Amino acid sequence: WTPLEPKLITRLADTVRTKGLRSPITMAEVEALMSSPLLPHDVTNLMRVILGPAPYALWMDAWGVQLQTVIAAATRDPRHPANGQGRGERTNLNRLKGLADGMVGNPQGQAALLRPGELVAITASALQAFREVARLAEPWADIMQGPSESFVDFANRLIKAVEGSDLPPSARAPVIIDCFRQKSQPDIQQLIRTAPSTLTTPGEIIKYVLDRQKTA
Amino acid sequence: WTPLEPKLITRLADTVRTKGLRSPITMAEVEALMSSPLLPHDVTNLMRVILGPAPYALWMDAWGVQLQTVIAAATRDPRHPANGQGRGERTNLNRLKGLADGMVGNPQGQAALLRPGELVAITASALQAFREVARLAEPWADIMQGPSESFVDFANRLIKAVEGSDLPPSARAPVIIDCFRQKSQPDIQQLIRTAPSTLTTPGEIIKYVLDRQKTA
Amino acid sequence: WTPLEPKLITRLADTVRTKGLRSPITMAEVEALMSSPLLPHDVTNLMRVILGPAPYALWMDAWGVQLQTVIAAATRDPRHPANGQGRGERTNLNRLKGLADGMVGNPQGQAALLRPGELVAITASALQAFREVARLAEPWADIMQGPSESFVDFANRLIKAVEGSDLPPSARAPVIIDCFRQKSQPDIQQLIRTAPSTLTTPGEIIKYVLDRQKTA
Amino acid sequence: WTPLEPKLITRLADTVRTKGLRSPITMAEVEALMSSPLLPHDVTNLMRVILGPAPYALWMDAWGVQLQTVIAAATRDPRHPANGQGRGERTNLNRLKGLADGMVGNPQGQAALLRPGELVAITASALQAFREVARLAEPWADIMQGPSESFVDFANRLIKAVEGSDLPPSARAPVIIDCFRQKSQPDIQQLIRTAPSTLTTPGEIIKYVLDRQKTA
Amino acid sequence: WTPLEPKLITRLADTVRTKGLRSPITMAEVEALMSSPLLPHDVTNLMRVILGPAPYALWMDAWGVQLQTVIAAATRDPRHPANGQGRGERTNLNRLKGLADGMVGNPQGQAALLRPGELVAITASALQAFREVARLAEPWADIMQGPSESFVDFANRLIKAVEGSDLPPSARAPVIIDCFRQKSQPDIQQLIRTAPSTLTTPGEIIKYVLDRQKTA
Amino acid sequence: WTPLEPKLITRLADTVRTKGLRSPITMAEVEALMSSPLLPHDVTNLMRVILGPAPYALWMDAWGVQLQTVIAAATRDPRHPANGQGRGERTNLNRLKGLADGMVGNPQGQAALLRPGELVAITASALQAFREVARLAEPWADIMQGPSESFVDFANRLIKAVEGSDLPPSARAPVIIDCFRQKSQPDIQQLIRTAPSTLTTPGEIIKYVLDRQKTA
């Protein structure tokens, strides 16, 4: 086990302190420090340092919930990269949260007994939990394209607010499309309306509008 | 599998944030971080971090299209460095996009089953897709030299707009020359017209005009 | 013997100077510079540089007390990794504090005669002493949510004061919950009281209150 | 022999230029760059660069005096880590100051003939000389605890001024205690007076006061 | 082949952006990044990134002209470090500009087939071309030594303006001498006039004046 | 042949630009970058980059003179580490300045044919030439302590002007002492005169005066 640099952690903590939890630069920095698969000890201490007390409590809750969803999917499929073929390799939440025997407080033993699939699952779970808490701590139907705003900025803002909301995953694309059509001030509205082809995806709509947009 | 440094990724993300997607320094930095053959996981997370939501959607589209062209060329030639000799090594798009069995979400298994030819093909495809999206996201025949503008500023603006346009590479120099001759208000027009030597390159025209220009 | 970098020591000293002795980032940095087993000379000079005069006196006291507890456990078990099997390898406090013969002021001789078990015991003792002094140097039942204060600030302040106090670790969550319920002015008190679900964690209470709070 | 980085030396010189010679950050930085045992050449050039001309003269004087005290202790004990067992290894001041044969101006030969005990003795002597000159270049009985000042700051200031003064080493602890008792405004005066135990050490007094102090 | 760091290239580009092309600090930085022999790909991309469009066109022109002079000298001497002994190693401009077979667009193959003499000749040619373009993008006979200016600054400015001008190489030293004698306000004029020795070189004049100058 | 880092060269150039040629930190940095034996190409380009035009001319002159002295000593002793035993290894100035056959402009061939003794002799010659030019490019007996000036400032100024002058090294301390005694306005003059001890060192005089000075 090799610890993360306290210099990088200090820089990330100051980034979270000045920019906040939800800025795209902060999420990019977290993705950067979330590159190599981390042990539960690493992620736990990282969130202890970069997050305040109340966001840290929220993040512990969300991380537990996401890990429980992962363990449900694992008991729903014996071919999980964290699982094994026999029943003796089934992964309990004590092993994921670092609470199992031979792991409590010891990162070396942790790194010894853990699987790489276990590590990547823990890491993805922690990233999703961080996203949830960031969206929770500090409205997509109120988003309009400003008179002077470009279209890529409007699309970025709208997709961000729609994907970071309470909608089901299967309802985001139709909502994004129908918001492109009704928001996005009447020049682009008419540009999308008079589309000789049928656009059935936000990416296709974005490409079409970027091609035929009024250069100004 | 070894992940890319989040420090390099953060620096590249800030480069894309300040300079944009199309600057030659940004493309050089991307080529730098595109040096070793990356696994689909690496490139996917890299584009997730450095690109905004809408450019990321566009890039996913373009990457899929380029990979499909690659797979068409692969079924058109059984000697692809990603293919094998027998039919059992034919490479499906699920294996290229990282969607095949034993690869979904697991970078270690990905690195296990993938071929080096597969990796370099994926990498070249991703680079071409990035170029397409950069050219797509953010008029040379409307550029005139202002009455008060200097000539080097006009030349910079014109060369920028001509090279960052939809012209073929072999048509930029003649267009730049003929735009120097017809734009560039009539004092410099007559200065270029009465050139005892024949100027056959934008650099030579710029040098001549800078030598014989009316100091004012 | 190889000395620690004065650059790392200077950075750690400035960290202690700005963040204080008790911040989790400071303890993480100390754990980082406490990774390899240090000789008494190293830890002594490190604490001389990073700590002020009075905290250094306190730390010398605490380190002596912890080393004495270690030596009592060592005379209570002849199988200490610092001890040997015969009586001639029993470790005296002069050998632990670096005061024994051939060690006073000489780090090379120190590194020569010392055991790895001796080094790790000295290191753990010094870490525990640092924790004690940090807890000692610089009231949770008096914390109320102000009439104009938001709830996340109140939760941050309360969790800080409860975790940085003299309570056992197993008594912090119930106290934080019961302080959320009785402090946190009667609007939020009634909001928590009328919870159709049972909230059994500070994170869950924080999430619920943030969801259903009166936007104002 | 490997030279110290001129970048670190430049940073240390600017630190000495802005903060002064006596600041605790400056002494910490000097301790940092005084980590590995330096050859007389290294310390001499370091003090030549970081110190002005007059402080450098003072430091040469003080270094000579401290080295002479070291050589007196060495002739008073044939078991010095710089000495040897026979009389042929006795260390002369020409060998300590780098003036001996085969060493004058040559750092490689210096590093060849010098002992590690010689190096650490030279280094400790130079550090003590730096402390003396810093205390000399730019009053403990005039120190009072301000009405708003905390007790650890007052203790730090008092111990600093008492240890960096002209008192004998055997008279510092009683003076520090009796200054804690008579300074340290009457609340802490009465707190120390009504001590059911007898406090016979500055560390014990500091611990007691920090325990029973009026939180405010 | 190893690429240059995009961090160094970004710093150099910002240096060129703020200080300009002709500042001595910029030329020093270019000399720094021109230390190891670069392949045509490296220098071409470097000038593409650090220079604007019009200076880049000018630089391509000047680089071609200087490489043509080099190839003329090469056909004038079969002992060029880029040439070989037989006629089959004669170096064509397609091989120098990176246009030869097996080199177009491929830096690895470039580094494979190129000679070290080829690399150093290309590098020196590119440096001279950069100097020409910098002197061209933004008068010696108008330079006077100011009443308060020192003599070394005046000599630096004069030698810079004379060597970066349109004079033949064999006419710079006499002009520099005769400008030292007639400029360089009458105190130094009389100091040079009453020289018991005959000064026949700018360096000798500078040395003499620096020796006998009026300290003030 | 491996080139020096342009980053180190840029840092050294900025050091020379801010601190000057004669500062002890600058000479230390030059000694640092003069550690490994450099080829004539390396030293020539280094001095071209870090020095201005006129100091570079002066340095070329001084380097030639010092190399000529070296070659005179070499013809005065056939056992020079640059020479050989037979007459066919005698080293000409064309081989030292890098002007010999197979070396002009080619650092690789240079490194091939040159001897290590040749390299170290060239390096020492270049260092001595740099020292000469630095002493030449930029009065102690006119220094008085101003009526309002402190004594440490006067001592700094005097020691600076005496050590940076044309006196032999063995004549600086007596001159500094006798200038302390006769300058340093009559209050300090009488303070030094009535010294019950004999002060035989500038540091001792400075310490005595700082102790017994009239606080004002």
Image: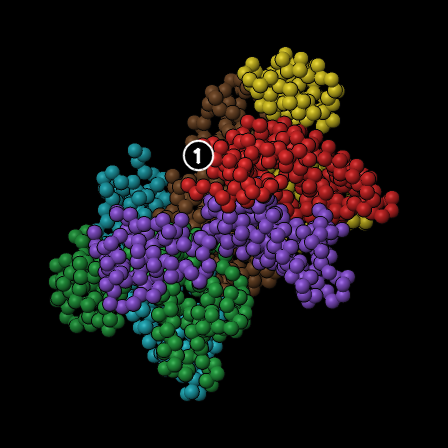
Chain colours: A red, B purple, C yellow, D brown, E green, F cyan
Which residue corresponds to the image point at 38% horizontal and 81% vertical from the top-left?
Answer: E75
Q: Residue E47 is drawn in which quadrant? A: bottom left
Instruction: Give the chain letter at badge 1.
Output: A
Q: Which residue is nearer to you in this view: A75 or A16?
A: A75
Q: Residue E160 is drawn in which quadrant? A: bottom left
Q: Residue furthest right?
A: A87
Which residue corresponds to the image point at 41% horizontal and 77% vertical from the top-left?
Answer: F103
Decide: few, some or many residues near mark 1? Use Cα within 10 Å; few <14, some 14-19, many ≥20.
Answer: few
Q: Position of residue B156 (x, y in %)?
A: 36, 53
Which residue corresponds to the image point at 46% horizontal and 85% vertical from the top-left?
Answer: E87
Is residue E22 among the parts visible in the rendering? no
Q: Which image quarter is the N terminus of chain C in?
A: bottom right
Q: Establish if B50 lies above or below D191.
A: below
The amino acid type of the residue labelled 1 equals: Ser
Q: Position of residue D156 (x, y in %)?
A: 51, 32
Q: Establish if D52 lies above or below F60.
A: above
Q: Position of residue D25 (x, y in %)?
A: 48, 40
Which residue corresponds to the image point at 52% horizontal and 34% vertical from the top-left?
Answer: A189
Q: Establish if F74 lies above or below F203.
A: below
Q: Which residue is nearer to you in this view: C52 or F205?
A: C52
In the figure, is residue A121 to the left or right of A50?
right
Q: Residue A104 is drawn in which quadrant? A: top right
Q: Which image quarter is the C terminus of chain C in?
A: top right
Is residue B183 among the parts visible in the rendering? yes
For label 1, the residue is A148
